[PDB]
Image (spheres, grey):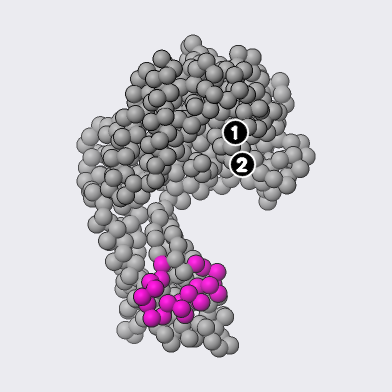
Amino acid sequence: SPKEILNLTSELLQKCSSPAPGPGKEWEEYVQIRTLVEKIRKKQKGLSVTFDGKREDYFPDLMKWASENGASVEGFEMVNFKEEGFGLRATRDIKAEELFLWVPRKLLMTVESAKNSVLGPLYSQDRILQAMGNIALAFHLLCERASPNSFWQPYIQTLPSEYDTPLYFEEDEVRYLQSTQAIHDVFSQYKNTARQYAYFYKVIQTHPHANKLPLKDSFTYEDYRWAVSSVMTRQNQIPTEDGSRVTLALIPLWDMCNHTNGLITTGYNLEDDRCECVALQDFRAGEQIYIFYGTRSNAEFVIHSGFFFDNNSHDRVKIKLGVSKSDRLYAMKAEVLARAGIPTSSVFALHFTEPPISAQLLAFLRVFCMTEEELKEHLLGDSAIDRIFTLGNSEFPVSWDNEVKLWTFLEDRASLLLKTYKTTIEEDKSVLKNHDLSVRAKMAIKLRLGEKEILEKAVKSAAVNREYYRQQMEE
Amino acid sequence: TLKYPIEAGIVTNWDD
Ligand SMILES: Nc1ncnc2c1ncn2[C@@H]1O[C@H](CSCC[C@H](N)C(=O)O)[C@@H](O)[C@H]1O
């Protein structure tokens, strides 16, 4: 039996180590990889270690554990919510800015605790663990989960047994994402995970420093999927004890908070060596305590956490823009962009929330549409440096004609990008309104709809700005 | 100002 798994993993490693296939074969390759993984998944027993009963049965112990190591356990409780899963509920009125959550370092799971755990020897021998702190944390989590008397066992036994990351999607759920940007990242994720599994399994079956690890007996694809999905759902960057460096960590109590729009209210206290979180807003007793995870896109939320956030104030799409080398004004535009601290060619973001384009993108577009005289005015003269310094400011345009040109180009580009999607916005809305689909299918369709909606809002904003500057020019 | 703001579930590169 182990030899057939070894053959399957060797094939998976070889296929996942091939160069990137061309556009249009990507999906096929993905499906191919899926196939192999499924076979491997079908001959294994799921997670190697499972805990009988339901998750909530373990939440007291966690609290108790945290309580006995210096963490705050007063003022909140673990509660199931329909729209968010398990989370923190205030048992007492909590005022805004009130320090209400703190977790000392001894409770955390870091790369440092991984190096000094049972994984230590293999970590000191394996190159991928040394380079990839997140994979190292995932394997630390795996190894501690299989250790009956681990210090973090009360925390591990409260972790979810599955996630809604694309690694758990059915194939037809992923097919909804075809012709989007996000799907490529999905592909990446899958490929990476697959390759990594095929690598580490081989390592675990051969390296001597892994013989005393609990993974030598059993190490399934579902184990690694769970580990990496737990880490990418819950990893955080924290300073080391002296503060000179950064490391990855899992924060047991605080990572049960759910997300809402707001500001970061979580920081690390080096003197008291503990993570600290103050209330995002006033939470009365019985009200759910939320935090703001970060300024991540809905694509990142779905791919690295497993949920789509409605009314995400920081939602955006990638756009690839550069100055053409066929342009006779390429050198002057390149020099102006360099002086402004902006690359000649790069990836920018289109945001839903006003303004749809950033100061960086606005300055790039203005240089992109400059005439030779305007470029000269921005490259030579006493006023040149001031004009390039106001380049990203909406209040200080280069010329009405430049604005009209740039907004025309942006509108046309966003409309073309819209034309490159398989479905329209109204198709997606109709599907979401009239069809009942899985949670994951709803996430995929809302994601593609959000991409196209950002593009459509860019189209309309560019049209309105083009008309505004045309009208100013007419008077 | 928080000297070390902590992002929940920060994105890292998984391509080894
Ligand atoms: N604002 C939100 N809306 C819907 N789901 C959310 C959410 N914030 C967090 N989640 C869910 O919670 C996970 C983050 S870890 C937060 C704890 C989680 N609810 C649990 O029971 O273990 C995500 O995978 C997502 O599924």
Q: Which mark is residue A278?
A: none
* Disc 2: host chain: A
Reading the image, the residue beneath label 1 is A126
Within-10-Å neighbours for mark 1: few <14, some 14–19, many 20+: some
Residue A122 as seen in the image, left or right of residue A104 = left
Q: Observer-nearest residue: A424 or A120?
A: A120
Residue A398 locus on image (x, y percent): 45, 80
Evaluate if marks 1 and 2 touch, with contact meaning CB atoms under 8 Å apart.
Answer: no
* Residue A452 as seen in the image, left or right of residue A241: left
| Extreme residue in the top direction | A52
In the image, what residue occupies the spot 59% across and 37% down? A127
Which amino acid is tagged 1? Asp
Q: Upstream in the sequence, badge 1 or badge 2?
A: 1
Q: Residue at x 48, y 86 (%)?
A: A376
Q: How many marks?
A: 2
Instruction: Judge whether residue A253 can be spotted in this image.
Output: no
Magenta-drawn stretch contains A323? yes
- x 57%, y 43%: residue: B7
Residue ID for mark 2: A237
Residue A39, given in percent of the width and then of the height, sits at 34, 23
Residue A96 lies, with reference to residue A365, above or below; the image says above
Q: Chain of mark 1?
A: A
Question: In front: A286, or A63?
Answer: A63
Tag 2: residue type?
Gln
Quick one: label 2, few (<14), some, or many (20+) residues within 10 Å? many
Spatial CA distance of label 1 from label 2 is 23 Å
Secondary structure at numbered mark 2: strand
Q: Going by the image, does A234 lie left or right of A269? A: left
- Compare residues A157 and A21 and report the one nearer the observer: A21
Start-end of magenta stretch: A322-343
